[PDB]
Image (spheres, rainbow, N blue to C red):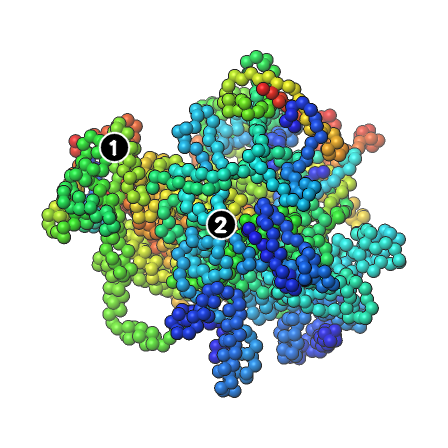
């Protein structure tokens, strides 16, 4: 609720979520400010389409937003053989709103490492009407080393795969 | 032989002279005409010395620029609760306090006119409250009542400044609030009456009407003021040669080590070791800066801590006595934001003003600062930065500036428990960041 | 009689652009510079001149230079009429101005009253609170639609909303006006306030100020925040009390005399203001010199010996700070991630030692690089923190010496003494070059690409030896691996190294003993790296195969077990490994990358990883 | 640190000169002597140790 | 009428925002929302009588940007001949594909 | 204003008029008898010295707060002066005025608002004020000299309304005389005017013990915790009415110089008070270090403090300074 | 607007001067009569108003006979005439969405 100017009224100004209908936030580990806002995002999914009435009007907007997050364990990924409630600092109910806890791991692998290591170095090698067209085919071929259906058309059918 | 235009007349001589009594009491009774008579005399009495020797500044140029006189200290007054309405054109001798000022607005001493003919540069005088205008053309024999325009930025104007005063509360009977009165100056007594000092003014009296409605000429509780003729305050040096000869014998004396050791303490107990640092801090080297590389200044930073009540302040007060330009710290009158970087709303225009900090303000002195065990840790944050780069970096949304500060410091701490509690490592008593130990 | 006087000063000025103003022939300094002032102008088409006060003083010996201070405030349209007369005779949409500069005497703002009206007086000061860019008029062609509204009227003065002089036919005059937008040229300006300097303020005595209009190409050239000088024409301004909705102090006591004009009885007051014309802010073979200096051989060692005289020895730390000073590459993959722009190197060590010297060195040496201590961790600065509402706006952006390290290498010390909240905040500021904020107001994405450089403190002041740095880092774990290696400075109480450092330090604070010869200057190193930045060196050789094995050998060492140290030098560090390698080749100006160049890249981290390992 | 305060400052010494001439001012018989200041230390001992009961 | 602030992205930082005015047109109403970043393709009309009241009266004119079109938040500003417009018309060749 | 004189500098006939209410209008120039009625008329303007001017001063009254009913708050009233009863009233005068009554018109925005409102004042006629050194007073100075009895009868004289405590009633009378410490001559501004503080929690209403001394001692102003706090203990600049604003309104120490500063409630508003007590114990730095001015005035006043303990009783078996929060202000 | 009943032609005047003679007019104020004027707003007795709204209010102009009788917080009970005054729709032009009929009670 942004306050009024002199001849105005206490109006309602949205922030992040009411803009982002189909988007992204982030909650990893703001440890001090964890108890501040986590009581405002786990009621965005549970009590889906949430709005509030501080010192103003009692309305309720609509927000069918999507959440992703990139949390970070305290130190290493296997901080314990002990389970996930020992590993993360979150508790159960806010954790239980999600669908899956995708977890990563690697200790030591010869063939898997080059499969990253040979892979990553070739990416750094990727650093007038005909010429405007000819740069485009160069821009088309440079994405088409294995030709995995490039982004010139791929995003374009997503928007009507959702509507 | 100096050329100045000002004679500060004591004007307490006509009562000490057998004649000029009727002059003297007319002076306290018509004080606009009688100065205008006396300004004709001094220019003519200057000619009365000019007619003696005809080799005196070519007899023209010191006879064109006018002079003026300044009667002062005339009679006495007592305050402001005596200003009766009959005192219409009299001399008044105020004793009070200047508070705040304003920049100069201009006056109307000469006008200019031009209508839409090819060329007309008349310059009408005013000398009144009434500008008079023509309604017929000029510069031709047959041209009608034309549109006369007012080319304002051509005719010259002098200065004028209004200054607000409030009386010094002198023997006020513990119930009355000191009220206000204003000033008006005309001559070059501007920029010498800075706001914040004791004052004794010598002025005449005048009252003016006010417009009641802002857009009518209708008017009736009047406002008065005073018009100063001469002011007086509450009370690169010109280096001579007898001082240099006197100091050089003092510089020839072996005892200057101890003669300056004894002279800083007219009352203080002995404690010779702190007398070396305090003296040498004021004798603070110079700025031996190279052209490329270095940028080293010879400034130092002594400190004292330990036993309370060892004239900790009066020694520092003694240092403030011997420095003409320095700063004095406050008891929590400053903070992390109350030092510099200001967004204050002044009562004159409600706009921005960046006032400097006390640290940059002592550019040419020694910053005296205290209560360092009790200074908060939101502050005690910029003095490290002035301890390294001699500057203040202002992180304000108004502006960015790495303005320097050519300033020197001493520190005066306080213990915590009772004392310096020896047979203990005393650093654990006085808590302090080990970075600023360096 | 003054008409010919202005006509006298017209041609006398004109012949000055006809005569020479040059004393030296063919030792540089080509004769007749004002014709070159025309000819530079007829290419880039900027519509200025730039005349000095020296050469007009030393032409008439003050017969005219004392006259021109007291004519041009009235005779603006005389000198400019003359230069219009001379350009037709010389050159073939044209609007000009007259820009004097460099009068001798510079005053302060407290010395401007009586003689200063219509004069020319250079004024110093500092500037605060700019405003925006709007257009002005100076000439219109508005007229009434009585019969014909095509009368180009005159007198666009301070109240110019009434063109009412000399109508075209015998029609109704001053009946209307139509200010078209189609035929009258405009000129753009802004209104600014100034303020008095800090080395002149007598006491803290509410330091007074005034305002100034700058109107030519001077627009958006006074950046707010500098010690600045000005042109000098002083001017008064009224308010005419126009047809708008409106028409303590005894102000306008002067203006009570100013009553009874031919229009309505009021009080027209005044205030002294300022009009400027020209701003300033005081506060080859050299292009061939690079081509010789690029063709040297030992300039890698010449550079590392010529960094800073404030330290002796330790060539390891000196090699690092040079590479930080230059930039690497930042261009990366198509459609997605922007990779790292640079390398970030910290140094730990005992305080009150040689650590402070580099910090003192770079902030005057680097382009626009800033320095903070970071103890102010809760208000703003390091932590980017929104300001509260002021003068009609809540949620505005803030300062902080982080988002202004554009082409700057910000420096910041003492990581131990701050809180825990910033330690994830700058951790976000390290990986990708943006930061995000959505604090009490809309979201913000500011892309402040940066290059940090740090100097924190050990846990005890003295560095442990038998242990590792995992205990003496005094930070958390993932920001270590997010960083490169620190090149820890060690110390010793040796009876020889002290005396030589004593002799090394005593010549420094000599008043003059400049016997040390750095082979490069401050500036000729500065332009040299400015030649170095403008390449894009790409590897093309087969040392990619040579690259991948050594890291594959490297990572199998520091992984001492399945449950050993989590200083596991991962796939992040291949990027710094190659982006150091293009940077060191950007020092020796080679575009291809040899397998020989990355060899010393390896042993830079071999010597680092032994300083990692016990 | 049980009961008492102070460690005998000269600021206490100069104050005991201050109140003596004060009591020599009110009871002026021009007798600034040992008995006049004996009235003074008579007050500092009863002001102190008011906590010992 | 949407008043506009400069978005604090590509800006030499440490300073203030600046203000303008946008007058939309008929079929361009409420396309944007209060808070995103946008860009406009307007003309530059400078119509005013010459009455202003925060500052004094002067020979000064004020700007008004009458817009002609509007697009949304753009991203990855590196293109040269595409992804500058949300063209999004999939009719004969695209939809068959 | 009561009379007028316009001069036109042609005829010198000074046109007179009666003075009406607070707004009036000058007349023309073609109205006189000599300088008028021709093709040339002298243009009128004013004159100061030929215009007799009177005195004028405005004041407001309230009610005695004892004859007010149980209900509403009291209200003000407007009063004027004429003649020469001026400069004879004061803020805080428990007085009465006798005078005559009349209402006044408003002459501004009289159609939409200001229908037939009246807003009267009263006009003054008389003031009967009430309750106000070797000059016919020496007979009572001899009564102390003949009877003597300094140390005890004067001790029973000031505050005889308590039980015991003759030691503390003696400790104060010495400080109610003070005196110049030493005429130092040279620049050695020595400390004067020692300050005594009290502590303890009796139930005998300790406030009216000390403050009753203050309301009979000379120039000793009362204060408390609320109101003039340690920032408004000195003077400052504030809001005023439509007359001359930004005056230097004071607190206590800029007006109670060289007297008694009888304070209570020492745990109240201590963020400003702890600065405020040191700055007077430090000699001569009572100032206004604001953005308005940097002028510094004197400091010569004694301090009498009474600190209240912590919860319940001060435990004497516990450590002292458990309830006073200033070690550095006390022990030195 | 105080005679309570008859809407007479008002006299938009404060005080006249110079009746049809050459005599400077004098006014006797002891024989000029006065009266007072006090408005007070009355809330709703907040127990018998049913629970769908906040309390409302109207106002009442009384005269001298029962002034200072009304302490704020009294269960009062007044009775008077219902009355409108003020020009609604003509005293300004175009008069869009402005009530010009104030509710008043001139009571006893």
Left or right: where C272 falls relative to D22: right
How many marks can you see?
A: 2
Q: In the rendered image of this protein, does residue A10 appear above or below residue B118?
A: above
Task: Report the front residue among A116 and F155.
Answer: F155
Q: Position of residue C506 (x, y in %)?
A: 37, 64
Mark number displayed over residue C239: none
**How packed is label 1: few (under 14 Cα within 10 Å), some, or many (20 or more)?**
few
**Letter of the chain that mark 1 sits on in the rendering:** F
Q: Residue at x 81, y 52 (%)?
A: C177
Task: Establish if F180 lies above or below E25.
Answer: below
Question: Is residue F53 left or right of G106 when viewed as pictured?
Answer: left
- Asked if residue E77 is positioned above or below residue A71 in the image, the reply reads below
Q: Which residue is mark 2?
A: F55
Residue at the (58%, 14%) spot, across then down = G49
Please, what secondary structure does the residue beneath circle 1 have? loop
Image height check: is C196 above or below A5? Answer: below
The quadrant where residue C9 appears: bottom right
Q: Which residue is mark 1?
A: F200
> x, y percentage for residue B312?
28, 52
Q: Position of residue B266 (x, y in %)?
A: 25, 61
Kindly identify the residue that appears in the image at 47 percent across and 48 percent down: F83
Task: Name the subunit of mark 2.
Answer: F
Question: Marks 1/2: CA distance?
Answer: 55 Å
Q: Position of residue F38 (x, y in %)?
A: 73, 62
Q: Is residue B145 visible?
A: yes
The part of the image, by quadrant, that contains residue B298 is bottom left
Residue count near mark 2 (Cα–Cα under 10 Å), binned few <14, some 14–19, many ≥20: some
Residue C299 visible in the picture: no
Identify the secondary structure beneath mark 2: loop
Mark sitting earlier along the chain (1/2): 2
């Amino acid at each position: 609720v942004r306050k009024d100017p002199i001849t105005k009224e206490w109006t309602l100004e949205g922030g992040a979520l009411v803009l982002a209908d189909k988007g992204v936030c982030l909650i990893d580990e703001f440890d001090k400010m964890n108890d501040q806002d986590r009581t405002s995002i786990h009621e965005a999914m549970e009590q889906q389409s949430i709005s509030i009435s501080k010192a103003g009007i009692v309305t309720t907007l609509q927000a069918r937003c999507s959440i992703i997050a990139a949390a970070n364990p305290n130190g290493g990924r296997y901080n314990s053989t002990l389970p996930l409630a020992q590993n993360v600092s979150l508790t159960e109910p806010i954790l239980s709103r999600f669908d899956i806890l995708c977890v990563v791991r690697d200790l030591v692998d010869e063939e898997a490492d080059e499969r990253l290591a040979t892979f990553v170095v070739d990416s750094h090698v990727r650093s007038q009407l005909n010429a405007r067209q000819r740069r485009l085919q160069r821009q088309r071929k440079k994405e088409e080393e294995i030709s995995p259906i490039p982004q010139e058309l791929l995003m374009k059918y997503i928007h009507y795969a959702r509507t | 032989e100096l050329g100045t235009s000002n004679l500060n007349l004591d004007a307490r001589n006509l009562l000490a002279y057998k004649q000029t009594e009727d002059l003297y009491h007319q002076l306290l009774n018509y004080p606009q005409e009688v100065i205008s008579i006396m300004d004709q005399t001094i220019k003519d009495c200057m000619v009365s010395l000019i007619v003696d020797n005809n080799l005196d500044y070519d007899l023209d140029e010191i006879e064109t620029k006018f002079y003026k006189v300044r009667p002062y200290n005339v009679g006495s007054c007592k305050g402001m609760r005596e200003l009766n309405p009959n005192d219409i054109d009299k001399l008044i001798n105020l004793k009070g306090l200047v508070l705040r000022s304003t920049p100069v607005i201009p006056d109307m001493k000469v006008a200019f006119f031009k209508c839409n003919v090819c060329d007309h540069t008349m310059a009408v005088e005013i000398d009144r409250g009434v500008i008079q205008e023509p309604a017929r053309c000029e510069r031709i024999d047959c041209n009608e009542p034309n549109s006369m325009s007012l080319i304002h930025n051509r005719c010259s104007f002098a200065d004028k400044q209004v200054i607000k005063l409030q009386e010094t509360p002198d023997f006020v009977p513990d119930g009355q609030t000191p009220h206000s009165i204003s000033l008006c100056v005309y001559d070059e007594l501007v920029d010498s009456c800075r706001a914040g000092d004791r004052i004794e003014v010598t002025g005449t009296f005048r009252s003016i009407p006010i417009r009641a409605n802002s857009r009518q000429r209708v008017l009736s509780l009047y406002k008065t003021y005073v018009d100063v003729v001469h002011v007086k305050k509450v009370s690169v040096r010109q280096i001579t040669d007898q001082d240099l000869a006197k100091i050089r014998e003092v510089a020839a004396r072996e005892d200057l080590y101890s003669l300056l050791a004894r002279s800083i303490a007219p009352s203080i107990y002995e404690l010779e070791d702190v007398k070396k640092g305090i003296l040498l801090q004021l004798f603070g080297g110079t700025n031996k800066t190279f052209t490329k590389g270095g940028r080293y200044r010879g400034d130092i930073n002594i400190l004292l801590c330990g036993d309370p009540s060892t004239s900790k302040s009066q020694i520092l007060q003694y240092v403030h006595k011997i420095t003409p330009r320095g700063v004095y710290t406050s008891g929590k009158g400053s903070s992390a934001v109350g030092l510099t970087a200001y967004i204050t709303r002044d009562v004159d225009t409600k706009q921005l003003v960046l006032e400097s900090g006390a640290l940059v303000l002592s550019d040419g002195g020694v910053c005296c600062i205290d209560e360092f065990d009790k200074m908060s840790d939101s502050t005690r944050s910029v003095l490290h930065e002035v301890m390294e780069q001699q500057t203040i970096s202002i992180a304000k949304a108004g502006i960015i500036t790495t303005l320097n500060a050519r300033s020197s410091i001493l520190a005066s701490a306080n213990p915590i428990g009772s004392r310096y509690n020896p047979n203990l490592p005393v650093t654990e008593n006085i808590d302090l960041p080990p970075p600023l130990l360096s | 009689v003054d008409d010919v006087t202005g006509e006298k000063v017209r041609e006398a000025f004109e012949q000055f652009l006809e005569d020479f103003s040059v004393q030296s022939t063919d030792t540089g300094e080509v004769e007749k510079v004002y014709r070159a002032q025309i000819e530079f102008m007829k290419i880039y088409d900027l519509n200025t001149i730039y005349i000095d006060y020296q050469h007009l003083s030393m032409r008439e010996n003050g017969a005219l230079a004392m006259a021109i201070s007291e004519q041009y405030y009235r005779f603006l349209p005389f000198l400019q009429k003359g230069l219009r007369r001379v350009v037709r005779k010389y050159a073939p949409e044209r609007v000009f101005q007259i820009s004097f500069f460099n009068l001798p005497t510079v005053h302060r703002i407290r010395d401007i009253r009586s003689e200063k009206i219509g004069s020319l007086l250079s004024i110093s000061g500092t500037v605060t609170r700019t405003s925006e860019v709007r257009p002005e008029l100076y000439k219109a062609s508005f007229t009434c639609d009585m019969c014909r509204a095509i009368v180009d009227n005159v007198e666009q003065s301070f109240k110019y909303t009434e063109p009412t002089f000399c109508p075209n036919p015998s029609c109704e005059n001053r009946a209307f006006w139509t200010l078209n937008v189609t035929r009258s040229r405009f000129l753009d300006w802004q209104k600014v306030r100034i303020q008095e300097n800090a080395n002149e303020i007598p006491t803290g005595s509410m330091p007074r100020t005034l305002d100034v209009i700058l109107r030519g190409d001077s627009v958006e050239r006074a950046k707010p925040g500098d010690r600045c000088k000005f042109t000098g024409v002083e001017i008064v301004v009224p308010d005419v009390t126009q047809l708008g909705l409106p028409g303590k102090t005894t102000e306008g006591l002067n203006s009570g005399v100013t009553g009874l004009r031919s229009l309505g009885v009021r009080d027209l007051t005044y205030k002294i203001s300022f009009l400027a014309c020209h701003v300033i802010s005081i506060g080859s073979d050299e292009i061939n010199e690079l081509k010789e200096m690029v063709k040297d051989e030992h300039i890698y060692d010449k550079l590392v010996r010529s960094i800073a005289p404030a330290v002796f020895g330790h060539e390891a730390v000196k090699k690092g700070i040079l590479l930080q000073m230059l930039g690497g590459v930042h261009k990366s993959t198509v459609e997605g991630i922007k990779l790292r722009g640079d390398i970030n190197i910290c140094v730990v060590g005992d305080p009150s030692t040689s650590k402070s010297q580099f910090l003192k060195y770079v902030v005057g040496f680097a382009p626009r690089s800033v320095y903070t201590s970071g103890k102010a961790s809760s208000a703003a600065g390091l932590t980017a923190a929104v300001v509260r509402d002021e003068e009609g706006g809540d949620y505005t952006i803030e300062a902080g010496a982080l988002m202004l390290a554009d082409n700057g290498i910000c420096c910041i010390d003492e990581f131990d003494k701050m809180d825990i909240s910033d330690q994830v905040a700058i951790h976000e500021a390290m990986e990708q070059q943006t930061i995000s904020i959505a604090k009490a107001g809309i979201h913000a994405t500011l892309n402040a690409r940066t290059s940090i450089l740090a100097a924190a403190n050990p846990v005890g002041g003295r560095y442990n030896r038998k242990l590792s740095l995992r205990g003496n880092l005094n930070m958390t774990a993932p920001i270590m691996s997010r960083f490169d290696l620190f090149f820890v400075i060690l110390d010793d109480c040796n009876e020889k190294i002290d005396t030589e450092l004593a002799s090394h330090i005593v010549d420094l604070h000599m008043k003059r003993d400049e016997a040390i010869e750095p082979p490069f200057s401050a500036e000729q190193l500065r332009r040299y790296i400015k030649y170095a930045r403008t390449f894009k060196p790409i590897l093309t050789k087969e040392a990619r195969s040579y690259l991948v094995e050594k890291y594959k050998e490297l990572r199998k060492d520091d992984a001492q077990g399945f449950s050993r140290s989590s200083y596991r030098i991962t796939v992040r560090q291949l990027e710094s490994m190659i982006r150091l390698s293009e940077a060191i080749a950007r020092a020796n100006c080679v575009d291809e990358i040899t397998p020989s160049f990355i060899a010393e890249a390896y042993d830079l981290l071999r010597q680092s990883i032994i300083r990692v390992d016990v | 640190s049980k009961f008492s305060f102070g460690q005998a400052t000269p600021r206490t010494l100069l104050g005991i000169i201050r109140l003596s001439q004060a009591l020599a001012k009110l009871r002026l018989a021009d007798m600034v002597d040992i008995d006049d200041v004996e009235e003074a230390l008579r007050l500092v001992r009863v002001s102190k140790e008011s906590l010992y009961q | 009428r949407v008043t506009l602030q400069e978005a604090p992205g590509t800006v030499p930082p440490g300073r203030l925002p600046r203000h303008r005015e946008v007058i939309l047109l008929a079929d361009l109403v409420d396309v944007s929302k209060p808070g995103e970043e946008v860009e406009v393709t307007g003309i530059y009309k400078n119509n005013y009588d010459g009455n202003l009241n925060a500052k004094n009266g002067f020979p000064v004119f004020a700007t008004i940007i009458e817009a002609n079109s509007i697009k949304r938040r753009e991203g990855n500003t590196a293109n040269e001949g595409e992804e500058g417009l949300d063209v999004f018309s999939w009719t004969e060749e695209e939809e068959r594909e | 204003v009561e009379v007028i004189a316009y001069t036109c500098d042609q005829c010198g006939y000074e046109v007179f008029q009666e003075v009406n209410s607070r707004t009036f209008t000058p007349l023309s120039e073609c109205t006189s008898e000599e300088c008028s009625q021709n093709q040339t008329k002298g243009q009128l303007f004013m004159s100061t010295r030929a215009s007799k001017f009177s005195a004028f001063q405005e004041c407001k009254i309230q009610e005695l707060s004892q004859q007010v009913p149980v209900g509403h708050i009291p209200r003000s009233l407007n009063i004027h002066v004429n003649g020469t009863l001026v400069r004879s009233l004061s803020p805080g005068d428990i007085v009465d005025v006798t005078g005559i009554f009349l209402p006044a018109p408003y002459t501004g925005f009289k159609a939409l608002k200001a229908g037939l409102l009246t807003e009267t004042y009263l006009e003054a006629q008389f003031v009967r004020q009430h309750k106000k050194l070797t000059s016919d007073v020496e007979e009572r100075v001899m009564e102390l000299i003949t009877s003597g009895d300094v140390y005890n009868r004067l001790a029973k004289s000031i505050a005889p309304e308590i039980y015991g405590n003759l030691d503390v009633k003696k400790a104060l009378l010495l400080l109610l005389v003070g005196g110049v410490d030493k005429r130092v001559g040279d620049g050695m501004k020595i400390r004067g005017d020692i300050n005594v503080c009290l502590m303890g929690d009796p139930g005998v209403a300790k406030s009216q013990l000390l403050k009753a001394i203050c309301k009979i001692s000379p120039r000793g102003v009362y204060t408390t915790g609320k109101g003039s706090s340690g920032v408004g203990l000195t003077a400052a600049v504030m809001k005023d009415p439509v007359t001359d604003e930004m005056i230097l309104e004071g607190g206590a120490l800029v007006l109670a110089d060289n007297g008694i500063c009888c304070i209570d409630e020492f745990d109240k508003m201590d963020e400003s008070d702890r600065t405020a007590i040191h700055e007077v114990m430090e000699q001569q730095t009572i100032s206004i270090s604001k953005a308005g001015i940097n002028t510094t005035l004197n400091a010569r006043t004694s301090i009498l403090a009474a600190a209240n303990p912590l919860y319940g009783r001060y435990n004497p078996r516990l450590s002292p300074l458990d309830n006073i929060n200033l070690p550095a202000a006390l022990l030195s | 607007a105080t005679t309570t009943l008859t809407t007479r032609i008002p006299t938009p005047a404060i005080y006249p001067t110079e009746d049809t003679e050459g005599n400077k007019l004098t006014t006797e104020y002891g024989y000029s009569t006065f009266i007072d004027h006090q408005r007070i707003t009355v809330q709703e007795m907040p127990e018998m108003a049913p629970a769908g709204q906040l309390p409302r209010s109207i106002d009442v102009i009384l005269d001298d006979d029962l002034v200072d009788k009304t302490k704020p917080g009294d269960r009062v009970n007044v009775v008077g005439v219902f009355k409108s005054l003020g020009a609604g729709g003509m005293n300004q032009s175009n008069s869009n969405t402005l009530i010009g009929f104030k509710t008043l009670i001139l009571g006893n």
